[PDB]
Image (cartoon, rainbow, N blue to C red):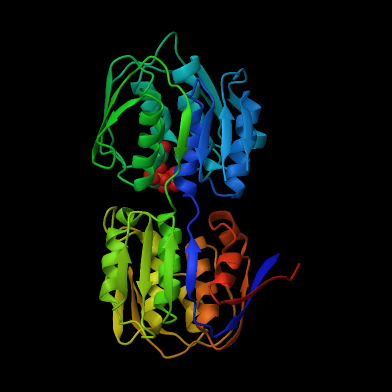
Length: 419
Ligand SMILES: O=c1ccn([C@@H]2O[C@H](COP(=O)(O)OP(=O)(O)O)[C@@H](O)[C@H]2O)c(=O)[nH]1
């Protein structure tokens, strides 16, 4: 059971290169299934889901290779089923569905448990495909989609916003006959990025990043080279790492425009920020941060994925700051952990009241959410003494070797075992 042993305090500073976004990488790999020619998917981080998708892909008949890149040649796909064995660990597996039937005429993805008493609905994908003209076949534990010929552009109004469904529907639509409109489509940068990837393969997509995405079906998708966008959340974590340690940090391979809310929020914290087209700088000038007020909300507003981090920030800044989760609930489980570190806060309903304190104290802490989990490691950094963060596999799944990046930042950190 991997644990993070952190020795603090230490001012985090210097340079950090941001990994590709796990959440743009995933949809793009599945979308690659659409490519009739070899594709170079660049800037793909090395995470477990990447490994899982690669397997799933190989299993489909696609020649799959990786490094910084993930080389994909899909023109041999002859197995149209993501088996229970492969999709078991990965929800995103569902993304195999649309590409399969849109390009091949059929696709079957396994629904682990599915109707398993607690199963995150996958209905949007299934129903989206249906609107597109796909024949659906449902039996406990699986979903089969097929179609005689091409998919049929359709007008789809989404009742629930879904990053997931948006990728499915938008992906299948690139091959369908005619035009497809997605109302209430997810607006996330990762969607814009997946759409851009498709346009790169010859697809006709517009409105990516808005509420309405329009897709004009085309003949076939080619190949090419494509760089996955940077990890916006990863970038924010690192910005925050310096913002709370009085550090100065430069984020390499970043993408400023995906962090409007986060950047403005840091300025409020008194941070000194500069940006270029591919880099972001944050400078505290040895200064402790100022308490800020935050409202997480749907993109492009303040990203809930930045919450645990800003909370931590507030917890060590000058003043009082309230962080309010407007959409999500129960997003404060990691706070008691921070309190065990000397932090002062009151969790009230969907909000956390923060009383910035001078210095944190080492402690054995733990969290399930990668973000909250990352914040703990961050805390270990600036806290007095020894901090041991348990079950860091959570972080390993979404952060590409955070310890290495942290060490180069001046952090005293050891990956240790408790088993
Ligand atoms: O087929 C679907 C897809 C999404 N959702 C709902 O929309 C939320 C967020 O969807 P999204 O695709 O953004 O994320 P995911 O569910 O993949 O974690 C989910 O938790 C569900 O509550 C649903 O009910 N059915």
